[PDB]
Structures are given as C-alpha cells and as structure tokens.
Amino acid sequence: MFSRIRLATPTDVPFIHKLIHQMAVFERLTHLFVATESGLASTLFNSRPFQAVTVFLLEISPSPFPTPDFTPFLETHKVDLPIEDPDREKFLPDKLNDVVVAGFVLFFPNYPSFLAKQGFYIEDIFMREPYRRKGFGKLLLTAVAKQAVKLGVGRVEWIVIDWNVNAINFYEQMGAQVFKEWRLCRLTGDALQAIDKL
Amino acid sequence: MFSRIRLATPTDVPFIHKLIHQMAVFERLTHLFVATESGLASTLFNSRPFQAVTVFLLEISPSPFPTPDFTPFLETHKVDLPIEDPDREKFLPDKLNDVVVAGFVLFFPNYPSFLAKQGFYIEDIFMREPYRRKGFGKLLLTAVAKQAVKLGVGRVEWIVIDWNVNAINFYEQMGAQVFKEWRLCRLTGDALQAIDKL
Ligand SMILES: CC(=O)SCCNC(=O)CCNC(=O)[C@H](O)C(C)(C)COP(=O)(O)OP(=O)(O)OC[C@H]1O[C@@H](n2cnc3c(N)ncnc32)[C@H](O)[C@@H]1OP(=O)(O)O
Ligand SMILES: CC(=O)SCCNC(=O)CCNC(=O)[C@H](O)C(C)(C)COP(=O)(O)OP(=O)(O)OC[C@H]1O[C@@H](n2cnc3c(N)ncnc32)[C@H](O)[C@@H]1OP(=O)(O)O
Ligand SMILES: [Ca+2]
Ligand SMILES: [Ca+2]
Ligand SMILES: [Ca+2]
C-alpha cells in the first residue's frame, strides 16, 4: 500500500474543511468551529508555500502514485488487515483513481528569537480514524521535519492538551521534547474588540 | 513622559539583539541564545510587516514625538519618579533626540484553523527593567491587539512558563484567557538532523 504527501492547493479546500471539522469533533471544540470553504480558500493561499500557512495532505493508494522548493514524499509499506473507510467518497481528489485523503498537517513559520531565525509551528496533525496506528501519522510529522531541514529551519514546535495522552505518547516516541510547565494564553476576537474600544 | 510604538527597521537590529539577550538572561535560557545582528537582519525582514515575523519597539521621550497599513501608536502618561537607566546609551536610535528604546514585542501570523483565518502569535514581550510596572508593557500588548483588529485578525495567542507568576498576572489583568493544561512540544535542530538521516 502506497502513500503520498503533497502540498494542498485550492481544489483541496473541501477536504481540509472536512478534516478540520473532524478534528474539532474529536477535540470537543466544535462550538469554536466557524471555518468554511470560502474562508479557507480566502486565507490559506495569500503567501507562497512555507512563507506562511501551509498544508500537507497525506494520500493513500493500493497502486503506485504516478509521476517549487518542494517534491512530494512517496512511501510504501504493508498494512495487516483491510482498511474500512465509511467516508471514502468524501475524500477523493479525482473520482477515477483510487487515491484517498487520509490525513493532513497544517503549519506555518514561527520565530524562536534566541535562534534569530524561523522555525515551523505545527497547528494541526490529524489522521482520519480508519487510518490511525498504521505508521501514516509519523510520515506527516517526518514530512514537516525533512522540509524544515531542506529550508534550514532551525526548530519545529507545537502544543498538546494533556487529556490527549495518545498524542503525547506519539510525540515522545517521535523523539520530541515535551514541556508541561507552559500555559496557553489567548485574547479572543471579543477580547480584542473590547481592547479596541479604548 | 511620552511613548511611541513603531515598526522596527534594519537599523534597529542592535537594539533587538540586546533586548533578546536581556530576555534570555532573565528567563535563564542564555545557553540557547545564538542570535547575532547579522542573523536578525538576515531573517526579520524577508516579508512585509504583518505577513510574517514583525517587531514593534516601544520608545520613551520627555518630549513629544515628531508629527499605509501602519501608523505609530503615540501616548503620554506620568511616572511617579525619574527613571534610572544604566544602559541608556545602548538604546538610543538617533543620539540627537532624547528617545530611548525601553522594550519590544516580537510576533507573527499564526493560524487557528477552527476560524479558517490568521491570528497573531506573540513570541516575545519585554520591558527593560528600569521601565517595568509603569504602564508601558500594556501599551505593547494593546498595540498588537489594536493592529489585529485593524487587519481583521481573529485571535491573539502566546504561551508563558509557570514560574513566571508576574507575567501570568499581567496577562490575566490584560483580560487574557490562561489555559494551564497544555504542554509545549519541540523537535530541536539536532532532533531534525537525526530525523533527516534515515
Ligand atoms: C491538541 C494539539 O494542539 S496537538 C495534537 C492534535 N491531535 C492529534 O494529533 C490527535 C488526533 N487523533 C489521532 O489519533 C491522530 O490523528 C494521530 C496522529 C495520533 C493518529 O496516530 P498515528 O499518527 O497514525 O500513529 P503512527 O502509527 O504514525 O505512530 C507512529 C509510531 O509511534 C508509536 N506510537 C503511536 N501511538 C502511540 C502511543 N499512543 N503510545 C506509544 N507509542 C505510540 C508506534 O510505534 C507507531 O507505530 P505503529 O504504526 O506500529 O503504531
Ligand atoms: C510571550 C512571552 O514572551 S512570555 C514570558 C516573557 N514575558 C514577560 O512579560 C516577562 C518579562 N519580564 C518583565 O518584567 C516584563 O517586561 C513585563 C511585561 C512583565 C514588565 O511589566 P509591564 O508589562 O511594564 O507592566 P505594566 O506596568 O504594563 O502593568 C499594567 C497593569 O497590569 C497589571 N500588572 C502588571 N504587573 C502585575 C503583576 N506583577 N501582578 C499583577 N498584575 C500586574 C496591573 O493592573 C498593571 O497596572 P497597575 O500597575 O496600575 O496595577
Ligand atoms: Ca489545532
Ligand atoms: Ca520567547
Ligand atoms: Ca501546562
């Protein structure tokens, strides 16, 4: 079984939208979800890949995939027993070919200022449920890491909520340092508007 | 006293460099500090202000300051006592004017994907020690917030380490939500290089 990691283009926004929604449901944050296709198309592609928000999609096929600062990551391995994907038809870029979008990673440049250089921050990493625990999720993280090297990015960072012990353990196994003694701070859209009123 | 918040340009790199170093010393992370003037100049200005890494400087004068997309935030207040700055001469953009760089805030676009829209992430906010607890630090945070509104950015976020009770309390008082149940994750430059091999 074969996989491909590629940059997302505007025609992928339906898939991104659906993946983000699935993530919100999984994380119990559906009430915060206001994203739309028009919204995503309106904001995801205002800069070059890797200059700002950037998305890799991971696609799977039983067949080999046929062939700017980027070439798609190809990889192949075995899976023990057959995948059962109820949402398969919702994740088909081209309805002819047996290529399914199984997950994504959404990231952007951050700036660890002690290094005086850009890093990458991973906002989202998500494998659809039928495709978890088969070695695909590590390919997504590895893709971001390898890309970072290719562009001389110094560091890759993200956060995780401590109820998500499975993701914590995944990250540990991937060789990530995990620092619990940080707190996430936020001025919401409403907090900002209130501050603006001064 | 009079204050001004403005965008940093390349000629400010010495001040930024020194402020970052002061922050590293304060945070007990000097061993991670590898930033140089050439490094900062090489990375801080490869994109338009607000498209990527962006820096505001806060400057203070006993005299009023000189009369697209950004205009400097001016403000005037009173200080209970005269300020004693031992490093004054290291933070003078011009030398003609009695204008001193007292702090900065370094931030960039993030992407809260449930909003399908950019936010701002504040990496660093720092007032030099002579200038703390006099109402200047809030002007820095307010500048980022007001700018976010002006550009229709949805959210402003950052993290804080839980030994830093003073900063935690500052943020709370500024109306920020503070979520302790998150952990910071990191693949270092060495972790990446290791992932790149094999
Ligand atoms: C909240 C935030 O800000 S960040 C986190 C965002 N949310 C998430 O990522 C969780 C969403 N739910 C999911 O299940 C995620 O899609 C995933 C990525 C964790 C799914 O798992 P995958 O990534 O496919 O795991 P993958 O198989 O690549 O794991 C790589 C290897 O690490 C190891 N590993 C995986 N999970 C674990 C675990 N829980 N404990 C220990 N080792 C593990 C295994 O050796 C695995 O190889 P395997 O295929 O033989 O199991
Ligand atoms: C994202 C990051 O970089 S996080 C970690 C680094 N950030 C830091 O803030 C730590 C660096 N060390 C410092 O001392 C910082 O320069 C600062 C920002 C805390 C300096 O303080 P300032 O920001 O100048 O404080 P400022 O005078 O603006 O305070 C504004 C209001 O906030 C509140 N406040 C300020 N400090 C505190 C405090 N220690 N406890 C409670 N409330 C406070 C008060 O209401 C204050 O008004 P008041 O003094 O009349 O009560
Ligand atoms: Ca996320
Ligand atoms: Ca910082
Ligand atoms: Ca924590």
Image (cartoon, coloured by chain):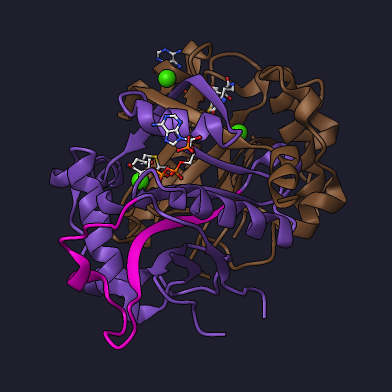
Chain colours: A brown, B purple
Quadrant of image for the N terminus of chain B: bottom left
Quadrant of image for the C terminus of chain B: top left
Q: Nearer the viewer, residue B7 or A19?
A: B7
User: What x and y, as percent, mark residue A178?
Assistant: 34, 25
Tell me what residue is drawn at x 67 percent, y 53 percent.
Answer: A8
Q: Nearer the viewer, residue B142 or B149?
A: B142
Residue A131 appearing in the image: yes
- The answer to if B102 sits in the magenta stretch is yes
- The answer to if B141 sits in the magenta stretch is no
Tell me what residue is drawn at x 56 percent, y 37 percent.
Answer: B174
Residue A98 appearing in the image: no
Q: Is residue B181 shown above or below A121?
A: above
Tell me what residue is drawn at x 25 percent, y 64 percent.
Answer: B17
User: What x and y, as percent, mark residue B18?
Assistant: 22, 62
Q: Nearer the viewer, residue B113 or A105?
A: B113
* In the image: residue A62, left or right of residue A41: left
How many marks do you count on the picture?
0
Quadrant in which residue A66 is drawn: bottom right
User: What x and y, as percent, mark residue B197?
Assistant: 25, 45
Quadrant in which residue A171 is drawn: top left
Q: Is residue A122 shown above or below A80?
A: below
Tell me what residue is drawn at x 36 percent, y 23 percent.
Answer: B162
Quadrant in which residue B96 is drawn: bottom left
* In the image: residue B179, left or right of residue A179: right
Q: Nearer the viewer, residue B150 or B93?
A: B93
User: What x and y, as percent, mark residue B22?
Assistant: 21, 52
Residues drawn in magenta: B81-110
